[PDB]
Amino acid sequence: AHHHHHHSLRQLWRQFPQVEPQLTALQDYLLRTVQLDNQPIHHKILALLKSGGKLLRPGYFYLFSTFGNAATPAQLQAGAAAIEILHVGTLIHDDVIDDSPTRRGVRTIQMTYGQRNAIYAGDFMFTVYFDQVLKSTTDRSLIQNHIDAMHRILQGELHQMDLNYREDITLDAYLNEIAGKTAELFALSCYQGAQLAGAPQSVIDRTRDIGIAIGCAYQMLDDILDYAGDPKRTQKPVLEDLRSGVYSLPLLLSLSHAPRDFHKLLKKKQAMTLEDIKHVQALVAQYDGVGAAKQLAQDYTDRALTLIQQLPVGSAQQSLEQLTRLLLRRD
Amino acid sequence: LDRQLWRQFPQVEPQLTALQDYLLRTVQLDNQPIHHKILALLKSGGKLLRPGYFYLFSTFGNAATPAQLQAGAAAIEILHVGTLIHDDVITYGQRNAIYAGDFMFTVYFDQVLKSTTDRSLIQNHIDAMHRILQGELHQMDLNYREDITLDAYLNEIAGKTAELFALSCYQGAQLAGAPQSVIDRTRDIGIAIGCAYQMLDDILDYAGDPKRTQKPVLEDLRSGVYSLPLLLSLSHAPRDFHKLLKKKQAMTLEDIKHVQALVAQYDGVGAAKQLAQDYTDRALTLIQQLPVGSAQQSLEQLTRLLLRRD
């Protein structure tokens, strides 16, 4: 999950004047894609859309669209909207599963209207998503690419679940997970923006590696924030993760330093006491799990930036580098 | 309706046999608790009824490959199963229903695409799923309503169930490239069948031996779900029903026996059967308008079997 919000980041779009209009306009288009008869739930979804801007994934999509001229603006707005609607559908379901009270400062659907309606609201967003996908293109490979992405995300979520409480979790298994659960929508955004615009092969062939690298680093930075600072201190989400068997990157990297000591604590699962939690954090600090996670996030970040520096020179290249350095805190 | 049903329809038996195995392979999954959510619906209950209508209608055409047809038929059963799993939601197992459902929707779209390069047939699927989910989102509002009209029930209860039946007949004929004559009748046929089918199930809530009915009916009533024979009985004694139904989740076994007793007194089952019979008759009449031959005869036999008009 993504527990941390970046201050430097919707107002973030002011620094990107060439795509702020598209994103501002997409926001309005987004408000009209959702036509639903149950007016109370329709209003709630609108409220989720209204209250949360940022539109990070549509941003990367629109930036990548600049490398080509083959796209109609109707296609691009539908392509960007598809990505964001899928994203929001998956958030609605995540919040049911986490029973989160609020999202984007809005009370979640299941709180006011119950779990069934919340689940069906997500499902309805999937139909809106596929409708927007079709509007965006008649290219069968690009539609399949969307479907395949939607599939990898769901597999990402299922494999993360299979992995709960596994103290033999590997870096390979972590990458394959945060690739699916997090990075895949970034890859999809970059690839579809560029493809839809018929950008040059050289660009197309880099989009997925860029999106994957960014999305991985992005998930790692959130994990790093879970264990950073004072090990005596505690964060609710982190406390809930450990009881639920979710070992994020700094812990994952620390396990092998003292598997029996971590196991004495982790095995208590939901029964883990607050003292237990702090002891876990003290071991992560002792073995510098955070410094290890940081080197990996930095290498993934630099891989993204290196690939971005190989794109065609110009405003979009420069905007992509600036956006990535900002998102991944590497200014 | 033994799960051996398709033995009586040999011209589609090889495709229905191949579909069952294709479906199983298609929905394979690591997580067992989630897989089992799925596997339960693929192994129990009615066997490939909607795909049966799909394939019978496909024998009017030869435009699609067997692989395309098979993805078309799978998509309908997958959507059916996806919605059934989510309809179960009310909890670690609840993680399971949600993800199992979501998994089915992603396989759904994949199969839809695999079935056709025709954009309007793809849109036809999305629109159907849209209507179904919109319908699901109206339910909370209908529950506990004792002023519900027959019109609302038909639109919101029978009509929703009808969607997958209409979708089946329509896509089977369209993908195979049946003549327009046939295509033009498919939705009217599937809607009448699907509505009759839902009504018959409702009839069984109150006409079936109480040996096993009152269990799930007790749950429906506590939840504010009033099936056709109850709906059609309310007007004969609105206050006497209200007195029981207003206890909602607090309703007892004696309160449900009482509701059941009043439905029998006021002939809700008889009223429901007469209306169901109109829809069944209509279905059979429309099927008798199709070109004469093997597909027509089989569609008739299947429909008479399903709607107990044999």
Image (tube, coloured by chain):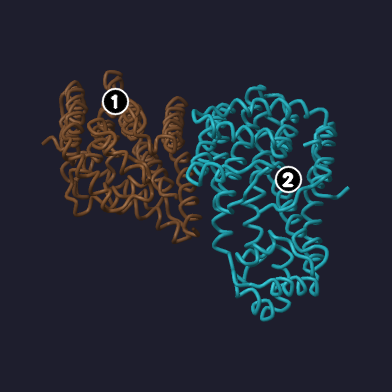
Chain colours: A cyan, B brown
Q: Position of residue B78 (x, y in %)?
A: 39, 43
> Is residue A149 at least partly visible in the picture?
no
Total marks in image = 2
Residue A73 in which image quadrant: top right
Determine the residue positioned at 51% across, 29% down.
A36
Amino acid carrying label 2: it is Ile
Q: Chain of mark 2?
A: A
Q: Quadrant of the N terminus of chain A?
A: bottom right
Q: Position of residue B122 (x, y in %)?
A: 45, 30
**SS under mark 1:** helix
Above or below for B265 versus A269: above
The residue nearer to you, when weighing B142 against B236, is: B236
User: Taking B144 as reference, is A213 left or right?
Assistant: right
In the picture of the structure, the residue carrying the numbered disc 1 is: B186
Determine the residue positioned at 30% across, 22% down.
B183
Q: Position of residue B40 (x, y in %)?
A: 35, 55
Q: Kindly give the residue lying farthest to the top in the view shown.
A: B181
Q: Kindly give the residue lying farthest to the right in the view shown.
A: A331
> Is residue A90 at least partly visible in the picture?
yes
User: Taking A4 as reference, is A150 left or right?
Assistant: left
Mark 2 crowd level (few <14, some 14–19, many ≥20, 10 Å Cα): many
Mark 1 crowd level (few <14, some 14–19, many ≥20, 10 Å Cα): many
In the picture of the structure, the residue carrying the numbered disc 2 is: A210
Q: Chain of mark 1?
A: B
The residue nearer to you, when weighing B234 against A291, is: B234
Q: Are discs 2 and 1 located on one and the same chain?
A: no
**SS under mark 2:** helix
Determine the residue positioned at 19% across, 51% down.
B210
Determine the residue positioned at 63% across, 37% down.
A83
User: Taking B302 as reference, is B133 left or right?
Assistant: right
User: Can you tell which of label 2 and label 1 is closer to the viewer?
Assistant: 1
